[PDB]
Amino acid sequence: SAEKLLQEYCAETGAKDGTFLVRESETFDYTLSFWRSGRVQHCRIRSTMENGVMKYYLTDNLTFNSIYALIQHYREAHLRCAEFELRLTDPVPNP
Amino acid sequence: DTPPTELHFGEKWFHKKVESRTSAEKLLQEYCAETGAKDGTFLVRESETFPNDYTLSFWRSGRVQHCRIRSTMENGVMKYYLTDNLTFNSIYALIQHYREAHLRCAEFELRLTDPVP
Image 1 (cartoon, one colour):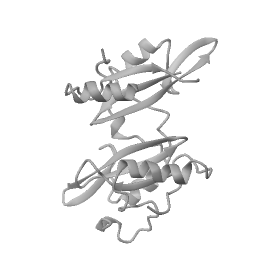
Image 2: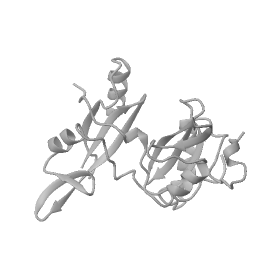
Image 3: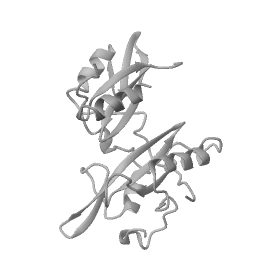
Image 4: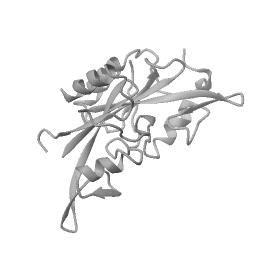
């Protein structure tokens, strides 16, 4: 899987954090995957209609006309992932 | 084995027994997958990668994220944090805070760099 492709390349390249690739969703959207401290992280890229025009985003308050524009922006500003920027809730009981 | 900064706090979510990232995800799946558990369901465990550090593992509809909780001494006082923007004197306080404010993990505090060829 793409998760593995990154694994290889990054581990076998000393690739710095931030090395990514964008893949098309499975049923819905695209998924962003990047190298970060030995692990491959990911975040869903969502889309919507903003006043009749198609947009993409990682977080609701900042949309883009395309995946290109979305990536380039997060190439100049640190990532934001609305998928995982949520509030903690219930604890898991026992180990 | 729980850190001294948590001695007087009730922490159902703290599991020093879960000694693996894989183990954490299974526990979360078993407990969350078909029980209707809310997103944000979590647990705290010792880091399997970084010494002295811990890891926050939570559930988000079929997904499990892991956020490193760094712990450093600052002027003779232990500080715990996800991002060095805000620190806490206990994991307890870090948890309660993120129960009222959206998470902001360090694994996302960076810019994308190069696309794999």
